[PDB]
Length: 265
Ligand SMILES: [Zn+2]
Ligand SMILES: [Zn+2]
Image (cartoon, rainbow, N blue to C red; front, side):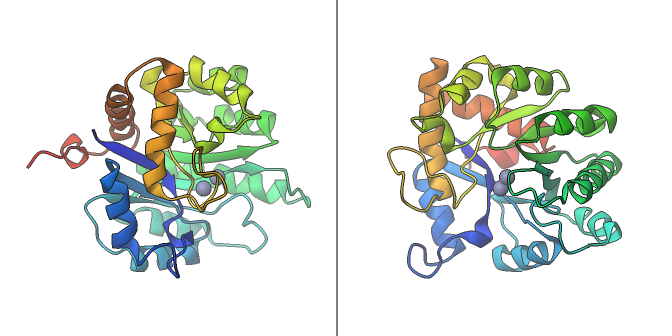
């Protein structure tokens, strides 16, 4: 079985006591057949740090961008354009909109989200979209900025089936995290059933949202294995089938050679 954790904050894990270092994390992941990860940075300075921390690895790819919640300090789109063109970067983001802690940065959040899409369009790399309490503004921007030009994934999906449908209509992929195993998450379980297999992805969004049976513990990439089994159960398929379909979807969306996503040889 070959699983991909499509969204994890490798620079945010506990390397003090939980893990020895990145090697350790990835080996723990490989032990549960999680053999590839997409490492996510939240700002440009943190992206630079992430590349140095992680180094050059065969089973890790990166996003480059500025999170919706990190829009108080300005940044130069020109730096985003340059850094996103680096080898290793397969996506723009995570970008999107988050109005939960809305101190009125939505105008800056929008401007940034628009730039991330533009750069994705320019480099033919998709956008990783984070959205929260900002449904209408998110779809408005996705449709208006022609995200269909570069493609993308609604990462850590927490909306409803109707919303999933509008996103699917734009070619989008929908990734589910451990939140889908939460007691209060029926709405998500409902969306999980609806999303076609060929548009599904899974992730942990580590270190947050550890899934059952590990709630209360720091999340780690290996746990995408539980997310996957859970989704398989909900979708009515074997985890090996979900693992191969989601890994094939990952390869298509992020333009990754299938050979890098297999364990033969
Ligand atoms: Zn996010
Ligand atoms: Zn994230």
